[PDB]
Image 1 (cartoon, rainbow, N blue to C red):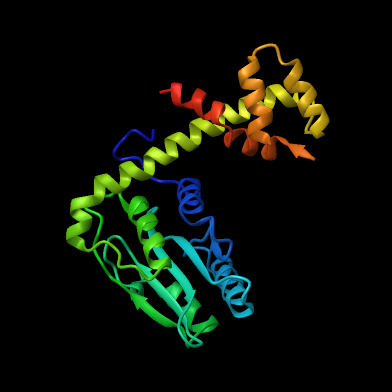
Image 2 (cartoon, helix red, strand yellow):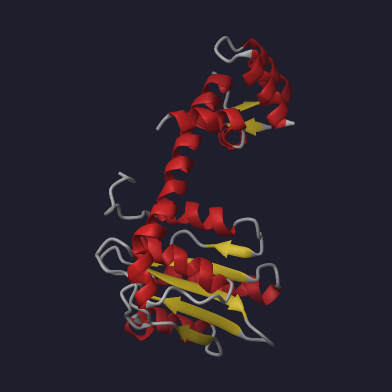
Length: 245
């Protein structure tokens, strides 16, 4: 339950937040699934990121790293000045990157020239706030902005959680309202044409003229996923999710 002050962020929660905050720059790679207990996948993941930076197709990567006991840590990897690769890291419990032997071995193998920037800053004050701090760290470290100090962290923990969870709640409700409208418009189809979508909007017996004409307007080869995404950007679907409060 997102309203619970002790809610543990999931992988999807962090992905949704990082996409929301950073996603307008397509040169930032947002990595979803990486865990220290999966060494082969970790090395594959870091190598892909380093190859995308080498080629110039990506400038930076933000990586929510899953450690022991469902703990989350923040790693960012960017092109530095000159020809440097900069690895910035912060564990919200203040534990050194050096404690993470697997990760240090991986990095030494793939990029032994990398500049390691372990901020080593205790931030969390309970067993539940890794998620909020990893998100706030990844956003700031990505742009070479200073992360919250131990004192600011203590002062801001509930505020940064509340701001992030407000988005998560809105995101979930808008997406649920968009997916339900998408289901009524798709009927027995997995995919529809623009023409069939418009037919289905004109024929719909529940929407009103304003909502149907705001819809075609707000809209200015379509799947459940792409139509859901479209409907989620529409003002009147956002209105319905806002009432669901």
